[PDB]
Image (cartoon, rainbow, N blue to C red; front, side):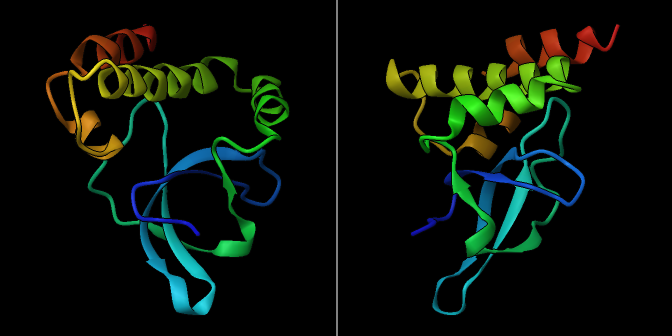
Length: 122
């Protein structure tokens, strides 16, 4: 039950679970397409292929554990995710915006957050 534009976790070998957004889902044969959320991304870069079985929903019970695991070697980076996802969920929840995470990242309303990130690389 992974829908397109949903937020998920994915683990590449040797790497910790990282958040991502779903772009394609091949519902009827166990595979999906996904793109990592990270401080600087291209939201128009096509989604690399995974399998449904390997995805956790972003808001699963494991969340807090998964987020700490990432803060081991990627504190600043996992920070950049949480900033974006959190900022996106505010616009959504406080009514200021209605599109998808990727649309958030491309729109002018992400600016104030992308600025902090992009510059933090400074």
